Image (cartoon, rainbow, N blue to C red; front, side, top):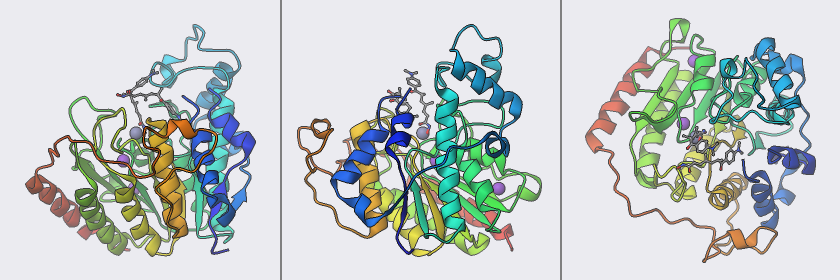
Length: 364
Ligand SMILES: CC(/C=C/C(=O)NO)=C\[C@@H](C)C(=O)c1ccc(N(C)C)cc1
Ligand SMILES: CC(/C=C/C(=O)NO)=C\[C@@H](C)C(=O)c1ccc(N(C)C)cc1
Ligand SMILES: [K+]
Ligand SMILES: [K+]
Ligand SMILES: [Zn+2]
């Protein structure tokens, strides 16, 4: 105990990048290269069963994933009806892949419930876009939702924090009408930017009003600003909501160098957000997500695992399998691009206040 659970397994990693460039392997490989796995408790992930996946997804949709997984993106009549397309490729293995991811996250939640640790990690998870009966944005199964549902079998109030560049709409929609789970997401909100939801006036509905928190941010934000913002909101959510457990997806598609070319963050900035949450001392389920500069994604998460362990890593990338992927420079640190931060300090303030306000109506 008191020692972090690391959901991994050579078979689990093979499955994650078995469709979608091999990224799971690079992440684990860099963590292993830093010997971080020796400081954690490695736990083999179970594979989610239909019942478990049905906790959120409809069987009609789950069955479709099987069908397609077994055959292919062939001219199937119901594929469009279920989100499969360019954004969410129909392929062989799709159902198995989802099931492994869903199980990994459910397994991590189990570890947290069983008191086996205070932090459980699943870097291959965090696919927050999936809907109950529809695929979206590379998410076939919403593992985060399944983890949250699993945690509730033990924790009264769950706080979901999504730091992916994209709005965590799949997760938000799932708990839109409840106050048992609060979703907070910092993301890019601009015309035509996927998924198109998450404006700041998006606060939830019914008993869920004010239990959905969204922070729209513009291109080029850097560590300092981000942390100011994120810490501002979190401090207020912790006071107003009083979570007993935390699910945190840390997609790296916000990091400088990403093909998404939106935010201008470094892993140190995200790591500060992570330390803040860790400080709370609550059961925490860490998830991955976006991140499409593979080498950059692994650099980031390897650094965050270090943060979790409270360990300092060396700037120099250790030699290992995918070593040549680490740049002219082969270092851990990432350098923010020379792009402007179009986040007007005034609007950011209007947002913080608007959120502070809505969090006022929260009383447990
Ligand atoms: C999103 C993108 C490029 C964006 C871009 O170029 N924007 O400008 C490329 C895809 C093919 C990709 O790399 C990927 C990697 C891992 C993954 N999972 C681990 C599920 C799913 C997809
Ligand atoms: C949906 C998304 C990111 C989601 C995310 O990060 N969720 O966390 C990115 C889209 C806009 C994209 O750029 C793209 C590029 C290539 C591609 N194929 C080659 C199949 C499919 C999609
Ligand atoms: K987000
Ligand atoms: K909610
Ligand atoms: Zn994303």
